[PDB]
Image (tube, coloured by chain):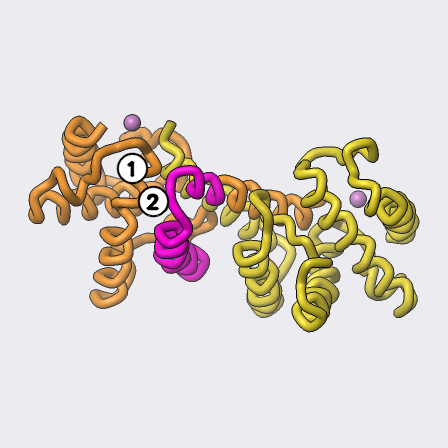
Chain colours: A yellow, B orange
Amino acid sequence: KHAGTMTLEAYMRFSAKLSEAKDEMGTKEYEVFTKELKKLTNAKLAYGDSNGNIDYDALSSEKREEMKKVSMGLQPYFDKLNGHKSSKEVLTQEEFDRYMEALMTHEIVRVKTKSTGAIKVEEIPEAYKERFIKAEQFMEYVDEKV
Amino acid sequence: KHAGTMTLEAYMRFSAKLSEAKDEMGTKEYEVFTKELKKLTNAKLAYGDSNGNIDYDALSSEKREEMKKVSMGLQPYFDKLNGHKSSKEVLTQEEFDRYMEALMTHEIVRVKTKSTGAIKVEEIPEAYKERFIKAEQFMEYVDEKVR
Ligand code: NI
Ligand code: NI
C-alpha cells in the first residue's frame, strides 16, 4: 500500500515507545540513555540485516569490541526499564562478559535463520547450533538472577 | 512488562520497514534516501512530542525553514514508495509549498490533539480548526492528482 507513510509510522511507534522511558528516568538519565542508544541504532542502520539484526561475528575485531562496549553500557538501562535488577551488578565481571556474548550469539542466530520470532534449532545452521543452545542456557540463568 | 526490550523491538520493526525500500531503489538511491530520512528522524528525536510529532510552529524561523526543505527533499521518495506520481512534479511550485504547509499543519494538529489516530475536529483547539480543515481539503486535492 502506502509503504512510504508506513515507514514513518513505524518510526513514530518507536518514538512513542522510547518516550515511555521518561516515566522512569529523569531528564539527565534519559539523555545519557538516548545518547548511548543512538550508537546501537546507528549500528543497526549500518550493519543490520533486513531486520536490523547485526552479525557481530562478521565485524572487524575492533568494531565488534566497540559494539560490545556499547551493549555493556546500555544493559543497565534495559534492565531498569524491564523492571529487573542490574545484571552488571548481580553478575561477576566474567559472567557479565559471557552474558554479552550470549546476547550477541542470539542476535547472530537471528541473522542466520532470518527469523524475528521464536528461533527453532532445526533452522539454525550447524555451525551455530551448540553455541546457540549454550547461549540460551546461560541467558535463562542470568534471567533467574535478575 | 519488558519495556526496555520492547523499545529495541520497535526500532527493529522500523528497520525492517525501512529496508523494504530496497525492493524499489538501487543502492545509490537508497543511500540518498536514508541520508535525508536521518535528518527527519533526528528532528523527531530532538523536537517530537511523546509520539515524535513535531510542533513546527514552535520552531525558530530558521529551523522551521530547514525542516521544511528536508520535507520537500523527502517527498519524492515517499511518493515513489507509496506508488504515487511525484507531487513535486505534478504540483506547481506554489502548490508544492502549500502542500508542505498542509503536511506540517496536520503534524502540528497531531501534537495539539495528542492523537495518533484519525483526528476529530472536536478535539482540535480553536486556534487550529479552520487551518486544519483547509489543510485537509488541500491534501485530498493533491491526493487526487498523484494516486
Ligand atoms: Ni521480567
Ligand atoms: Ni495510494
Asked whether the viewer can see residue B133, the reply is no
Please check the rendered image and state whether residue A22 is part of the magenta-colored stretch, yes or no: no
- Output the chain of dot 1: B
Q: Which residue is tagged 2?
A: B112
Could you tell me the amino acid type at mark 1? Ile
Number of other residues with Cα within 10 Å of mark 2, as a class: few under 14, some 14 to 19, many 20 or more: some
Apparent side of residue A42 relative to residue A53 in the rendered image (left or right): left
Name the secondary structure under disc 1.
loop
Where residue B42 appears, as percent x and y from the top left, is: 42, 60
Where B117 sits versus A47, above or below? above
- Output the chain of dot 2: B
Mark before the other along the chain sequence, 2 or 1: 2
Are the two marked residues, 2 and 1, in contact with CB atoms closer than 8 angstroms? yes
Q: What range is drawn magenta here?
A: B18-47
Q: Which residue is tagged 1?
A: B124
Q: CA distance from mark 2 to mark 1?
A: 7 Å
Could you tell me the amino acid type at mark 2? Lys
Residue B128 found in image quarter: top left
Q: Nearer the viewer, residue B31 or A18?
A: B31
Please give the name of the residue rendered at 43% of the width and 61% of the height, measured from the top-left corner.
B46
Residue A126 found in image quarter: top right
Q: Nearer the viewer, residue A126 or A34?
A: A126
Residue B57 found in image quarter: bottom left
Q: Is mark 1 within 8 Å of ligand 2?
A: no
Number of other residues with Cα within 10 Å of mark 1, as a class: few under 14, some 14 to 19, many 20 or more: some
Apparent side of residue A127 relative to residue B70 in the rendered image (left or right): right
